[PDB]
Image 1 (cartoon, rainbow, N blue to C red):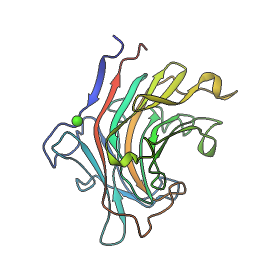
Image 2: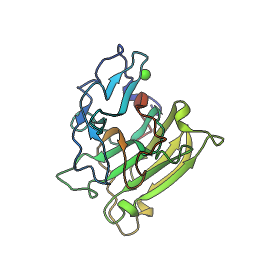
Image 3: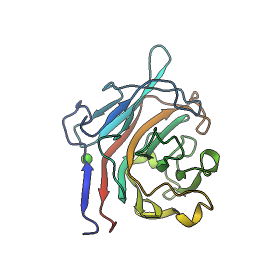
Length: 242
Ligand SMILES: [Ca+2]
């Protein structure tokens, strides 16, 4: 039935546990991420672990050698949904240069290169916009600066980093609609990509990360307070009649 929970990671477990490897991969390294990002993604529990309170915590840190570490976790090859309401409940980090995201890449990536394999950004935030999040799709002929994007601001001039909020896409054949705290803020359909190919009617895998630095967010400054935590209470996929 519509609204049935089809799949989830609720991040149950004791404080200091690793994320479940049957669900998540850790991407690693400080190269190739594009966007002039600074962070070195690691598989260390210093950058991703459960908190014992039912949350995944991804932590961006500055190391003694001046490098920044964080985590970038994906479900590639482990869980690849096609359609559904894809929702995470997240308390995002804050501060200049911090760039948290919950997003998806097409299952055919990288054999089908980006952006032909598709990318759906469910939530992105940049530190200089504590009251805003963005949702975007990238596809062939509509990618990068030409990604089809929308923005949601607030609540009541408040910072998203203050507490948990929900971020979702209601994803069906030929349509994606974005919701923050159950409120619509963006929508894209086969009809809005012009004469370009629609690449979203296929399985995608899920990604959670916190970047440090980038062309969009800019870079840490003297006000940036590290370490910063992104806390994720759950990632869920609900039946939506697809
Ligand atoms: Ca939980």
